[PDB]
Every structure is written in structure tokens, then in C-alpha cells.
Image 1 (tube, rainbow over the protein chains, first blue to last red):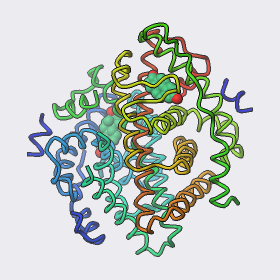
Image 2: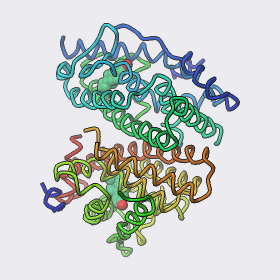
Image 3: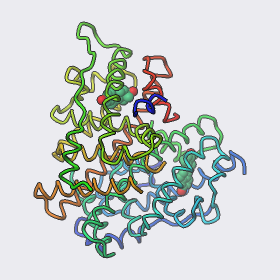
Image 4: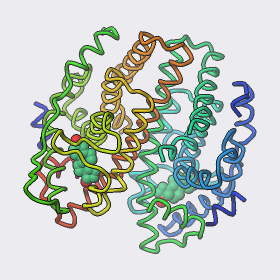
Length: 8
Length: 8
Length: 224
Length: 229
Ligand SMILES: C[C@]12CC[C@@H]3c4ccc(O)cc4CC[C@H]3[C@@H]1CC[C@@H]2O
Ligand SMILES: C[C@]12CC[C@@H]3c4ccc(O)cc4CC[C@H]3[C@@H]1CC[C@@H]2O
């Protein structure tokens, strides 16, 4: 999931 | 409208 | 209306309360639910006419607010009735449905889960009946209002009434403001659930899974 | 542990910038090109939104899964309250970007969008009527982030602190005790309207996607997908 990565 | 009539 | 005291507002709203009406296959359950909704709707109209300030509005405005808010009003009613039944939705005294029975209808369990979580929220807040009727009146007057001060003055009076109830209960100033906010934020969640429910009802209508009353059909297509 | 003044300073500092659209004034709009501009803008704002959310007190303490859920639930509400705020000083128009200021007649370019424009405009008008302040706006936007997905105890404590902060701001601005709870209620009831607009907007975006009107970024597809329309 892209948002999951972006939150990091 | 029915609602119109119900409101009287 | 604007000349009522807090205690008189509360008494007016408590007296205006509608009756609790009595009520598997997918068509069976949806038939039971929509049949109930249709009968509740007739009583909702009488209730609305007794919410202080509502009859001061034009017939056009009364129609608009009820078209906007009717499913929110049915849902907050359902959540209130279900508060004392963890994991269950008390649609009627003789129709208490558990969470898994929502799977009996397509797309319904997701809506059940949202309603159950709201009921659970009410329970953890220990929502009071006096608070519940204030919130329901706010839904009626607020949900369609952005489409001029009389309604807003009435809304301010209901806020005053909620705060009065909380002061009467011994909450501190800080606790009153916090609880007022907590209650009003639940109305965002009720709006969300109404929007999802309206989409679902529209989908059932298209499939002809169930016959819908003329009134319900008109309340539905008001949401275009 | 934050005071109200510290809460406000933190939120004001965390504010994202106002971005520009890719508007090309050499050509007329089509339904497709207008949707392209709006979604291209949304996608670039989302990157800033993600970084803003990490600066909202208490948000980064949540699990990554909870952070994902809250943003998935709230992202279009947050874009919309930002738009309505930007548009306050422009009666009858929506300031999507400094180079993309649209009225309702321009909204008619896209099937079904004028109805949504009308709701956003009405909300902007309500903000104006209330004289909404910047400090109040950033509190509301943070409340949307933490509340919208919260019913799907730490978060509630944070939400209570934002309530404290709103009242503090109103008190500091000289409102009477009664005016304070009345205005607190008026502001929070706006959030019901913003939720409503987001749900309508989400259905509209889904329709555009399903008619192949506009290519959506992978991120936007996943943010839309989260709403399982
Ligand atoms: C509208 C639905 C049928 C009628 C339901 C009802 C029926 C009666 C009532 O008192 C409350 C509710 C809320 C949930 C509603 C349902 C949500 C989806 C479904 O289509
Ligand atoms: C989601 C839409 C495109 C993106 C739009 C946008 C884009 C950027 C932004 O800052 C705010 C908004 C709110 C209105 C949104 C629109 C409502 C319907 C349309 O599909």
C-alpha cells in the first residue's frame, strides 16, 4: 500500500 | 409530494 | 420557541417522542426493515412538527429538512434503542438483530458494523435520554440548513439546553465543553452512515429485491 | 502535555503550502481536462497532507495501520475544508489554486460537479458568515483527521485537548461563556456538512474513474478504493 510507505 | 401532504 | 427555558425545551422534546413500532431471507429481512422504516416515517413527521421552531418554517423548508435528514433520524433512533444491547441492533422490540444477521443482506453487514460502533460509543459515553432528544432535533434542523437566523437561533437554544443538562449533572465547565464536542462529533458519523445507507437502499431499489412504498421512494429520490 | 497556546502554534506551523494547478490558459476546458487539473492538484496536495498529519499532536504515536485508516477516511474531507477556507475571501468562487479560481458556471463543465460546487460555495459562505478564524480552522482540520475514522482512548484524549484549545481561543477573543459553547457547537456542526460533501465527492470521483474520464494516480486510486464504493 502506497500510503503505508509514504507515512514512513 | 406525499411528504407535502403528510405535513398537511 | 426561542422563549422556552432549558427545562421546557427538554420537556417539549421528551413529549414529542415518536412511538416504538413493532416489526430469514434477503428479501424477507429487507422487507421487514423497509416496511418498518415506512411506518416510522409517518410518525417522524408528527414528531418534527413538535420540535420547537420547526412549524415556523415554510412548508418548502420543512419538506427540505426532512428529505435531507430522515435516514439520519431513523439511524440515531436505532442506535439509541440498541445502546443496552451490545452487539445487537434493536430495530423493534420484537426484532433484535445480531451483527452476523446483517450478512443476510448484501452490503448490509458493513452498515451494521458502523451502527453497532456508534451504539458502543453512546454506551461508553453513557448517553442520556435528554441528550439523545436534543441531538435528534439538531440533526433535523442542521443537516439541510446550508441550503436565515431563526433556525440558527433555535440551534443555539438546543446547544444551551445540552449544556444545561450537563451542568445539572454536575460536570465542570471543562467537562461540559468536552462532552458537548464529543456528542456533536458523533453527528459526523451519523451523516456518514446515512449517506452509505442511502446508497444501499438505492441499490436494493434497482435490483427490485424488495417493494418500496411510494413515500420511501420519494424520500429516496430526493437524494437524487 | 501541550498547553492550548502550544497546540495552536504547533498546528499553525504544520500548515501545508498553497499549491498551484497545471492550468493552461491557452486552451478551453473539457470535462476531461478540468477533472485532470483537479485530480492532479489533489494528488500533489496529498503528499503534503501526509507530512502535515505526522505533525498533528498524537498522530505519529498511532500504529502505521491506524494512521493509514484515518487518512484513508478523511483525505477528501481535509482537501475540502482547505478549499472552503482558501475560498472565504472570494464570494461565489472556489479557489482550488491561485491560478484556478472557478465559479459554479465553470463547474458545469464536468457532469454532476456543479451540485458539489454549490455545496462547497454554501459552506464557504457559512465560514464568512461566522468570521471563521485561522486558528479555529486548523483545529477543525485536525479534528477531522482524528475523528472521521475513529469509530472504525488516546485519540479521544487528543480530541478533548483540541476542544480545550478551541474554547481557549474563543475566550481569548473575548466571547462570553455562553457564546463560547454556542460557537463551539456551530463550528462542529460544519463537520457534518463537510462529511456529507466528501461522501458526495467520493461517489463523483468514483463515477469519473468508472467512465474512464481521467487517469488517476496510483495513490489516488488506493485512497478512493479505501471507500469501497
Ligand atoms: C435503509 C436501510 C433499510 C432501513 C433501515 C432502518 C429501518 C428502520 C429504522 O428504524 C432504522 C433503520 C436504519 C437502517 C436502515 C437501513 C440501512 C440500509 C438499508 O437499505
Ligand atoms: C473529488 C473531486 C476532484 C478533486 C477536487 C479537489 C481537488 C483539490 C482540492 O484541494 C480540493 C478538492 C475538493 C473537490 C474535489 C472534487 C469533488 C468531486 C471531484 O471528483
